[PDB]
Image (spheres, coloured by chain):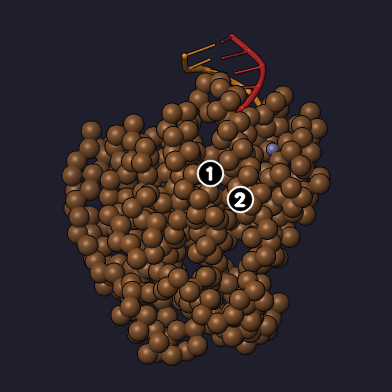
Chain colours: A brown, B red, C orange
DNA sequence: ACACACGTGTGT
DNA sequence: ACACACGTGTGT
């Protein structure tokens, strides 16, 4: 809508936009209700060159880490090359460090782990594997490997609408076999969490939130949540799951995704040094040489303090399946040397904390999560709860009338 | 173009 | 217990 192509990155404003970085701080200070050090903004640069290992699997090159307990809100922004207009700078990620009560995050971790390991039905996804479909990033033990579990409503190409188009009584929280008591406990946890996160979503990304509630009263059966204001329709739980680089292509246009992170008990204090850790990665971005306010020295101090961790290349042994998964293993050397030799190969990661809430337009931005050293969904290093709304979920009763 | 998706119910 | 049926956009 200005008079200033793919190489500048995807253009959208429903998370926030302004003429310069200072304007983004003004927006976020008003939205969040606090000023100054409570809000941190990082400039990130779109390169379009994807960081990945020699086997095609996700890597991080820089890690944005919470700088102190005084930092409450992290915002990643992209300045669009060449633009001087009202939307020259756009917001691509919002992270609330203190998202949900820690006692609730503690309880969800244990309850969801136990329920999903004794009754969970695995939901298969394309991003579970690399391009060649031969990696072992989830682990190779079927009893313990990382896995994804999907609930709520989902879009289906066979009905061009909700997958429950001809389900007399849909089970949004289906578990293995039939146990209504266990499914109701799981449903109660995730419905309560949907209800809690909706006001945070409205507060911090109001334009994306408002888009997601436009047809709430037209398709109530395809929405989660217990109170007025229901932006979500589906939720996926990921337990030690390595999401290879992808976009969520059938998410609705002009919406976003909210991610609630839960972590193992050894990674729940700010001063901690956990044994393992999973990161959320934007593979097409690099970090800036200046901080939010344009200072070179400020950015260097954040690198020395760990607030921005500059990683170096690795060479590790991994497994490679002898035959690809359709649609035995061997030990091979996997390295990231070439991704680190090129300064313009991307890989900006964030380290979300226990109980944090992350907001990003997963439909437009390429993203990934890193593989765990020893995945174990029975005692996961990280659980992510991923809340979204698919496209074409706007018909009553899961679109039963259209299907007829 | 063109292989590829956070599936379910009915049929045989 | 499989077997069939139902057929959408995006990235490349
Ligand atoms: O951060 C995660 O754990 C995550 C995992 C798998 C996904 O498909 C995601 N999609 C959008 C945002 C986050 C995620
Ligand atoms: Cl999204
Ligand atoms: Fe995703
Ligand atoms: Zn992999
Ligand atoms: Zn412009
Ligand atoms: Zn539905």
Q: Is residue A280 above or below residue A218?
A: below
Tag 2, which chain?
A
Q: Please report the residue visible at 73 percent of the width from the left and 59 percent of the height from the top.
A: A211
Number of the label disc, if any, that sits on residue A388: 2
Which residue: 50% across, 76% down? A40
Instruction: Identify the residue at image location x=37%, y=80%.
Output: A302
Asked if the residues shown at circle 2 and circle 1 are in contact, with their CB atoms under 8 angstroms apart, the answer is yes
**Whether residue A69 is visible:** yes
Q: Is mark 1 within 8 Å of ligand 1?
A: yes
Task: State left or right for residue A144 relative to residue A32.
Answer: left
Q: Position of residue A177 (x, y in %)?
A: 52, 21
Front one among A354 and B11 = A354
- Specify the quadrant of the image occupied by residue A26: bottom right
Q: Position of residue C10 (x, y in %)?
A: 58, 55
- SS type, badge 2: strand
In depth, the one of A52 and A369 nearer the eye is A369
Q: Are marks 2 and 1 on the same chain?
A: yes
- Cα distance in 3D space between marks 2 and 1: 9 Å
Q: Cβ of disc 2 within 8 Å of ligand 2?
A: yes
Relative side of A91 to A107, left or right: right
Residue on which disc 1 sits: A236
| Marked residue nearer the N-terminal end (2 or 1) | 1
In the image, residue A328 lies at what x, y percent? 23, 33
* Chain of the residue under label 1: A
Where's residue A285, x and y in %?
Answer: 43, 70
């Amino acid at each position: 809508s200005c008079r200033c192509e793919k190489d500048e990155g995807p253009f959208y404003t429903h998370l926030g936009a302004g003429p310069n970085v200072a304007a983004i701080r003004e927006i976020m200070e008003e939205r969040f209700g606090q000023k100054g050090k409570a809000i941190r903004i990082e400039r990130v640069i779109y390169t379009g060159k994807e960081g990945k290992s020699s086997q095609g699997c996700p890597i991080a090159k820089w890690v944005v880490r919470r700088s102190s307990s005084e930092e409450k809100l992290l915002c990643l922004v992209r300045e669009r090359a060449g633009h001087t207009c009202e939307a020259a700078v756009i917001v691509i990620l919002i992270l609330v460090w203190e998202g949900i009560p820690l006692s609730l995050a503690d309880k969800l971790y244990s309850e969801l782990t136990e329920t999903l390991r004794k009754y969970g039905t695995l939901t298969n996804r394309r991003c579970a594997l690399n391009e060649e479909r031969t990696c072992a990033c989830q682990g190779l033990d079927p009893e313990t490997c990382g896995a994804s579990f999907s609930f709520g409503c989902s879009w289906s190409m066979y009905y061009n609408g909700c997958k429950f188009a001809r389900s007399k009584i849909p089970r949004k929280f289906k578990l293995l076999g039939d146990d209504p008591k266990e499914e109701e406990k799981l449903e109660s946890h995730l419905q309560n969490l949907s209800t809690l996160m909706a006001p945070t979503y409205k507060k911090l990304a109001p334009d994306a939130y408002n888009n997601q509630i436009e047809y709430e009263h037209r398709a109530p059966e395809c929405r989660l949540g217990l109170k007025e204001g229901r932006p979500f329709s589906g939720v996926t739980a990921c337990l030690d799951f390595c999401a290879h680089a992808h976009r969520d292509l059938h998410n609705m246009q002009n919406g976003s995704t909210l991610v609630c992170t839960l972590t193992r008990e050894d990674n729940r204090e700010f001063g901690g040094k956990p044994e393992d850790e999973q990161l959320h990665v934007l593979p097409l971005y690099k970090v800036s040489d200046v901080d939010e306010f344009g200072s070179v020295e400020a950015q260097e101090e954040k690198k020395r303090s760990g607030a921005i961790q500059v990683l170096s290349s690795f060479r590790r042994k991994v497994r490679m399946l002898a035959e690809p998964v359709k649609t035995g293993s061997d030990e091979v050397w996997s390295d990231s040397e070439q991704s680190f030799l090129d300064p313009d190969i991307g890989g900006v990661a964030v380290a979300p904390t226990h109980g944090s809430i992350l907001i990003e337009c997963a439909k437009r931005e390429l993203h990934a999560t890193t593989p765990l050293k020893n995945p174990n969904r029975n005692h996961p290093t990280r659980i992510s709860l991923v809340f979204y709304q698919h496209k074409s979920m706007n018909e009553p009763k899961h679109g039963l009338a259209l299907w007829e």
